[PDB]
Length: 81
Length: 129
DNA sequence: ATGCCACGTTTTGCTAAATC
DNA sequence: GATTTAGCAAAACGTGGCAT
Image (cartoon, rainbow over the protein chains, first blue to last red):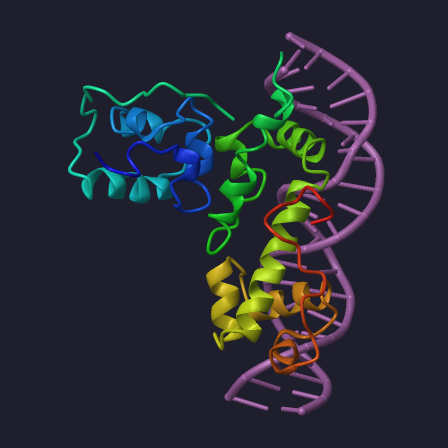
């Protein structure tokens, strides 16, 4: 599996307005992001279109499709901040 | 309840600081621009002020000022360019803002070696800066 | 909790000017 | 030439309260 795919969106090391805003949409894992529709996520009254570049980068560089259903992504310990 | 980490009134504002920082390099991104990233100017200002401690429009200028100052010392990017790039209508405008903030002219600040991190607001806006 | 006006303030905008 | 400055006006803003 990918080391950053199983990481929290808040700790993915991206831009300023991206990682922090993602964890505010009940997304504390990249696994949810890869199955999230950008057309709706980037339309949220907070998310910026400039964040799409970084978000799409993670999926593209990992070979993940838009809304690609993952077989297993949430482990034993999964909490929020 | 039972968290002792973040506040509900905080999380709604804990997604504005980062928004501004990643949108102040070129656009203005004031309360009216952040309206689509939160609530109406008059309401967002109140919420922002009661969370960060500083005013929104005040913060925008403060952060942009120090950001330009750094690019005047570390970088050699033209003042006119920095102005137009940061959203200023003219270099004269930037010169006015800079002088009324750092008290030192943008061009002089670039040559002042004694000048350092003074009045430099950081992208935190929660603990004095 | 969300929306708004008003008072005021800063900045801004605008033409120019002055200095280096 | 370059930079800085002269004022004027406006815009927003600074907030308070107000309204839903």
